[PDB]
Image 1 (cartoon, helix red, strand yellow):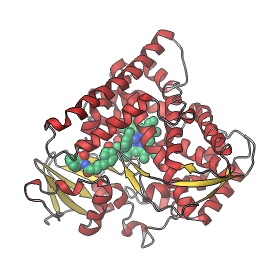
Image 2 (cartoon, helix red, strand yellow):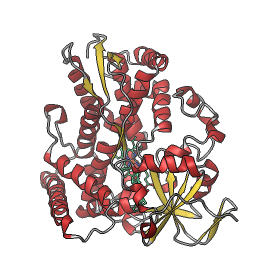
Image 3 (cartoon, helix red, strand yellow):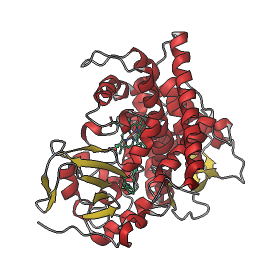
Image 4 (cartoon, helix red, strand yellow):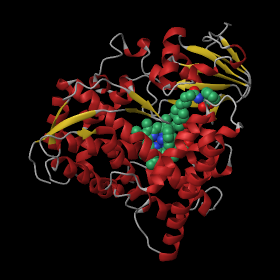
Length: 454
Ligand code: HEM
Ligand SMILES: O=C(CCCCC1CCCCC1)N[C@@H](Cc1ccccc1)C(=O)O
């Protein structure tokens, strides 16, 4: 039994000012490098413990001892994501009901049905790049976000955001980004009832209303038309939970659609951006991935079966997730009094944060080459120990979208490597912007077409 390390304090504000930064996850990573596998973090009326080692995270991932916690971030996002799957407690009736209805819509088998819609948006990206002039470059996170938002709009509810037709996001996206920004900024407000923030509160309510009205109108329009599409909205209007026998109601469907749009905007776009970053910084890896794309994607339109054969493209994605897990943390609570790691007594309800970037740098699992980008670490999935690699979270609360995200990212990265050579023309210095997720800010490349027809 051991005292937990704690970072530097600021009198009555305890550790809270350490996260008064636009890069709090990176700040916690530097704290974990200084203090090790566990540290306590105190704020007025709150204590969290940050876990970094596979030894402790494997215990935290025991669902008999720990359940998903809503972090204060997720509590603030719940003001517009409601009791959708991501912001619901495991014990809320709507969690298991939605989970049971939606699991079959997210299976590897279901990806066959979404493939044609993913191709539609991926071909729009490839055409955009084919149409750049010689003196032009690509804004990588900007284009990847146009792509993944459009893909989930089309597969989610047969709605075209038409992000490749725009400089300025669809108004829904404006309100969604600003609501996400307000949720994350509120973590840093030592005193949020100061009238200074009355404007933030009013803007936040107006952004929620924009989001509810598009989504409630889309649900209403689809029920009126009676149309049956191969999208998540049709599955949610028709599906019944085998346990309760109930379908989702319209309000909960709206929370799911908002949740899926947050995911498409924030996550897969980050993964593709990091993956392209690591490929242009590691040309041997780029050559090996481009060889696979050329050999496998032999048709102008990739098929579902061809995407499944892009093994090395999948290893590149996993290695990018290892170094920069675009969703960088998840929160747990102790279901009962327990001892973590034989050393750290916890009380029922005590909150843990898993720092996924630190888990993925545990040299006792990965070896001393942990900072190097080496997709070959993933050549043999069996060799990865349990709970060493957690970019999609844990157990029954793991990412329902994992097969969707990886199918889209593999398809798109495959097509990018088939169609273009890439240049790191600025010698880009990695600068990681934080929202809910991580993205490489300002990452730009030049593409040179291989002149292969679509
Ligand atoms: C590379 C892409 C993505 C990554 C890294 C990612 C990561 C994660 C992580 C870490 C969690 C666990 C959150 C927690 O424990 O608090 C999660 C949950 C979830 N993700 Fe994803 N995700 C991705 C893509 C998507 C997509 C495309 C969708 C939907 C279209 C989606 C929908 C969800 C939902 C609904 C949950 C909550 C599941 C539940 O608790 O029942 N994700 N994701
Ligand atoms: O560890 C953090 C800051 C990084 C969250 C990153 C997280 C946000 C969700 C999506 C994945 C990434 N937040 C904790 C602790 C906390 C609480 C109040 C004020 C300050 C910190 C929390 O939100 O409970």
